[PDB]
Image (tube, rainbow, N blue to C red; front, side, top):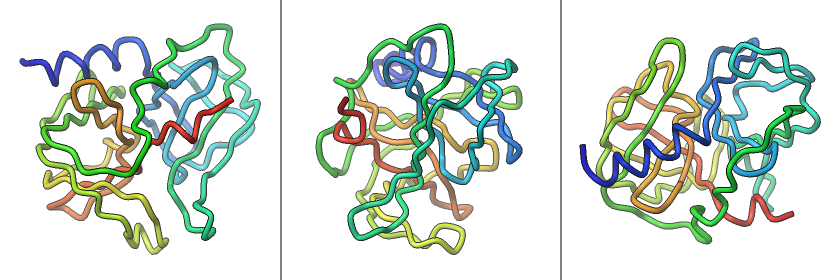
Length: 182
């Protein structure tokens, strides 16, 4: 509908796949080469389905901060025959607050879904499903089951992936440039 939705659509059309684990179907953001991200609660194993095709997992790393606190991001390298467009230059370098964000989801249940969530707070600490979690972003939208792994963007920046909600608020794990240096 406007330039926020334009940037979100550009990311969804080229840099997402549908990932399926034994814990469900997730929006999955491809970042560069064969490297993608997914919430850690997806419980990625040795094999994952990517757009309903059986795919070997070459590596999977559940990220934690240097205090050994959960960040809820798993970086996955996929045995896929095709690379993602490199979007690392759209990743923030530091923790921050944002205006006018969009949450975008693409699954069998929610295809081509875009939600204007408004202001995004650097919330920081969250007890997420009983697990102490750091680097959480918060938005005042009543997000639902099926949105996990959804991509949070502003114009020109990919800032996080949706990891949970409390019925009134939604929560995303930060994406930082420093996670994807090679």
